[PDB]
Amino acid sequence: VVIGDDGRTKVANTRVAPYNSIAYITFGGSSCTGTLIAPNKILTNGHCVYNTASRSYSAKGSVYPGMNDSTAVNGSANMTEFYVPSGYINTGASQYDFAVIKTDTNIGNTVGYRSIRQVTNLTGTTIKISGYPGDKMRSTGKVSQWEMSGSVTREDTNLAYYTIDTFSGNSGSAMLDQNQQIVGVHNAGYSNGTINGGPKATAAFVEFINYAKAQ
Image (tube, one colour):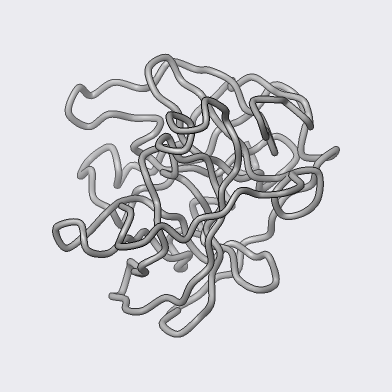
């Protein structure tokens, strides 16, 4: 959600790290954000790939790393396989709202990919959220990457929260620390639309990612 004044700014150059590894990702009826985490693997939210209400996987679409001004500046790849934690399929809970997508080509060798840092707690850490919000697409008529930084202001055992602005389309945007390491993934608005949040990169998160990376 957008909280008070909108602090997001357009990414100036998506040909450099970490922006080149952050992708606009499309499905049959929706889009999200994803981040390359291996040569042929994208991290996003579970809810982008699987709908708990309809018990249906999304249709496979395409991945555009560092798209800006509706231009595939770093090329594109197709989605071929989804990996979703059993926890998400069985509960739909935020603490499991992450997923990995395999691509048909090794596009991450060209643009790069981000490392994941296992954390316990994040409160007080400065993070950056960069991705592909739908409200900016409507207002500019172009698909571009938008970023904002801020502090993690509160947390529980599984989730971290922040007032960094997000909108539909940002689902799956990585929480990036100052070393460009992934420490969690944005998933939703919380507390009746007054704060944003998502799952931290806890032990359970990392275990699943390591499994998905080997497939």
